[PDB]
Amino acid sequence: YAGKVTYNASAWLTKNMDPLNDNVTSLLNQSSDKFVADLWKDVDRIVGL
Amino acid sequence: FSEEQTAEFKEAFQLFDRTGDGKILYSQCGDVMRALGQNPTNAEVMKVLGNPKSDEMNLKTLKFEQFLPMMQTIAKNKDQGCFEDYVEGLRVFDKEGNGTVMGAEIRHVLVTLGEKMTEEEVEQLVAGHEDSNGCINYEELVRMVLSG
């Protein structure tokens, strides 16, 4: 309504996907700190191939 | 020491007696040192005891003027273990770093390492300081032995 907006689409795929080295991540999962271990316990979602 | 508190120190020694005979043994010595104000390494005691085995440790007697040089020799004592050393001391078995350990390992390490404890020595010390997952948090357990 409030103006024609330009969006640009380069890199959006991996933005709606979020991939990472699952290895370092699974170790961030097994961390010491309550924060890092709460923050990263969600390892399942990271994609590797 | 002042004759003020030394009067009191004497009384607690006298209240350690078994019969009245004036003679607290090389055994109970450790508790008298404690109860006055100390927390000796069982080594600190053994040092001023003169290195006995169980036999003459049980058989040899002390009197107060044999004890007061001992209590005095420790008291103005070398290095006294802070909160910070102690937590890291228990932190050792935190498989990751968490701030927490299972009350089974903790009950055990004190019954296997350093100046080893009995179950009796451990349970009274530790119990009710695990949580609803059976983790003892060490940080408070350390503070507990300090302000006690």
Image (spheres, rainbow, N blue to C red):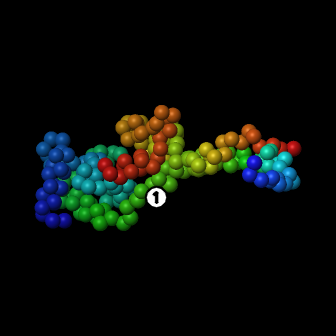
Find disc 1 in the rendering and name its residue.
B85
Quarter of the image with the N terminus of chain B in it:
bottom left
List x then y, in percent, for residue B87: 47, 53
User: Residue at position x 61%, y 44% from top?
Assistant: A38
The one nearer the camera, B81 or B14, is B81
Residue at image x 47%, y 44%? B137
Q: Is residue B26 left or right of residue A40?
A: left
Residue under the image location 15 percent in, 55 percent down:
B8
Q: Residue B110 versus residue A43: which sits nearer the camera?
A: A43
Q: Position of residue B94 (x, y in %)?
A: 56, 47
Q: For the image shown, how many numbered marks are present on the structure?
A: 1
Outermost residue toward the top in this view: B132
> Is B3 rendered above or below residue B105?
below
Residue B48 shows in this picture: yes
Q: Is residue B144 left or right of residue B21?
A: right
Q: Position of residue A18 (x, y in %)?
A: 78, 47
- Of the pair B57 and B41, the residue shown nearer to us: B41
Q: Which amino acid, by three-letter code, is at mark 1? A: Asp
Along the viewing direction, whichever of B118 and A34 lies nearer the viewer: A34
Image: B95 above or below B76: above
Q: Position of residue A25 (x, y in %)?
A: 73, 48
Is A44 positioned to the left or the right of A38 in the image?
Answer: right
